[PDB]
Image (cartoon, rainbow, N blue to C red; front, side, top):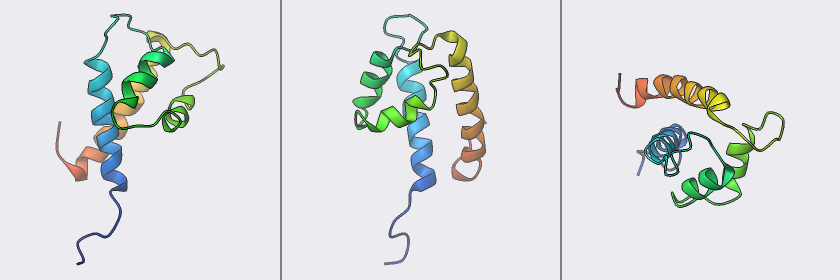
Length: 96
């Protein structure tokens, strides 16, 4: 029963972005173009994610702890997520 006993470490990363990128992008429910904790937390949560788990992933984006990130910081997010994705998709699965 070789194959793989446990891992999916890298794969998971792809699933997160793939699931987070679309969900949000294809979400702009309140067409606000901003990222309020409520929307993020709630949106991601239903994706099989817990309430606390998202805290660590999100907090990493708090610059001044002002708890407010508009299109200003949003660019950095998409930008950073885009590069990491490209490097990952390389071996995992094509895309570009």
